[PDB]
Length: 180
Length: 16
Length: 191
Image 1: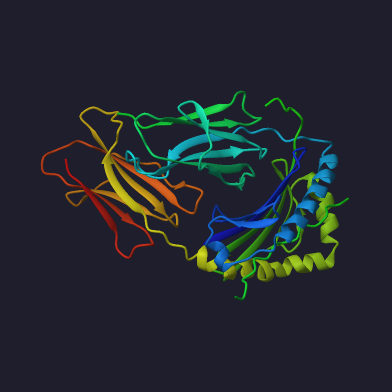
Image 2: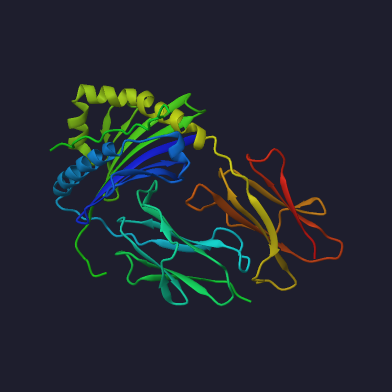
């Protein structure tokens, strides 16, 4: 098989969370921001070569929500079983002291698509320059997500990704430091 | 320029 | 978080499967309740089929709408082939050359042994070959890969470690073949 393009959407109750995205061979092409009602391209350059009418995605989500309510009743109100995430922290490239790099927090194999992710530097929450993806689909119908923290490697600083999910007994920490 | 449009499949109502 | 209320999830997936560009196209439309696929349209079959009892009422209701079945049947062209031509230039044709680095692991777990790392960073697409050579003979024993790691930003990384026994008179070469370059990338390490 050369390639697979997926249009993946979901609605989640009672969170009232809707998502609409396209995937190519496991990478996001774009998603629609439900609040701003606009197409957000994964790489800015993609928006130079294609366009998408976001209102189409908002109408699909209204139908998906209406259908979740039917399916919820038809199942005799069978709720989802929580599957907790696997979490990995690694850098975008080999670390060199005082050379800019990016920490990646990879959150995988979970459902439902609700997670609270925090970065810590030397035990304290940090938000400067952070970014994240939307929830990305898997063939087993679980989800993936990535969070990113740009940083200047030092021997002084240590980092953690903190992940909260309803399937976990306790919030998880995944630690990273550069030693010696 | 002439816009290259991504097309969405339309979701449809389930059996009521 | 102490929010213990039950959750209910509905997912829809429209999968366009391409074989030899747009020569063979298969559309799979999939409805998933919670984590269970209930009903689907396969363009090879040409109508909706229930995959669980939950989906029966939808396969019956949808299969009896002649124009919906027509639109879905044509979608392989109006949707899959259309979107493939719009996206082809920046997805199918995307090529990004790896950065290759060789260094001793900051962690040495095995005595009398130097663990060498070949780092291959920032490449697209996923298909890649990483091989170790010692004075130009290929080394296959003592090789350990992370395999392919998706960074989530349309790049991949992989780390391929070699367990070595250091000798005088040796050059180790990491060789990388990738569609983004016309001949292989090489990086040498010497004691």
